[PDB]
Image: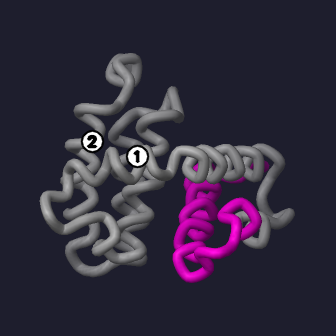
Amino acid sequence: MKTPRRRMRLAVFKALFQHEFRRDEDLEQILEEILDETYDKKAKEDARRYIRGIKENLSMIDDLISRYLEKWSLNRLSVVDRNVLRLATYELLFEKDIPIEVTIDEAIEIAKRYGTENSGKFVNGILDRIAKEHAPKEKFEL
Ligand SMILES: [Ca+2]
């Protein structure tokens, strides 16, 4: 049996979340602590691709998101909101055959699960805006 993408994405989120309290450590090493053999070969490869992509483009991703936050900057957001946005933005921009609504709706689920009462609505709004202006043109043709 194969590990679902949703479970793979959750491991990526957990690594992002845990890193916020261990900023002197490597995001990639934190992901490996989370990954184990209960995940299949592809899921571990996929989670690594996501974490590497987010880590290697973090400043670009953060600055991209920052343009949609008026004066309540990214650093002032909760750990959950900030990282769901980072994860979803990476997916919208670099994971080619995933429809925009799948990325946004599955990101909202993570926000509702671990965030506060307005987390889901907040991230849905920001991601709708980011997707409209930053998703590759081909993604709209899916
Ligand atoms: Ca279609």
Q: Which of the pair 22/99 is nearer the observer?
A: 22
Does the magenta-highlighted stretch encompass residue 113? no
Q: Main secondary structure of the magenta part?
A: helix
**Outermost right residue:** 37
Q: Which of the pair 97/62 is nearer the observer?
A: 62
**Magenta stretch in the rendered image:** 1-30
Q: Which residue lies under the disc numbered 2? A: 130
Q: What's the mark number on residue 89? A: 1
- Report the amino acid beneath label 1: Thr
Q: CA distance from mark 2 to mark 1?
A: 7 Å
- Residue 83 drawn at (x, y percent): 44, 64
Residue in the image at 34% along x and 60% along y: 108
- Report the amino acid beneath label 2: Ile
Does the magenta-highlighted stretch encompass residue 29? yes
Residue in the image at 78% along x and 65% along y: 32
Left or right of 2? Residue 109 is: left
Q: What's the mark number on residue 15? A: none
For mark 2, does the 10 Å Cα neighbourhood hold few (<14), some (14 to 19), or many (20 or more) residues?
many
Residue in the image at 25% along x and 32% along y: 133
Label 2 sits on a secondary structure element that is helix
The image's colour scheme reads one colour
Residue in the image at 27% along x and 42% along y: 130
- Residue 114 drawn at (x, y percent): 41, 77
The answer to which image quadrant residue 72 occupies is bottom left
Instruction: State yes or no: discs 2 and 1 in contact (Cβ < 8 Å).
Output: yes
Q: Earlier in the sequence, mark 2 or mark 1?
A: 1
Label 1 sits on a secondary structure element that is helix
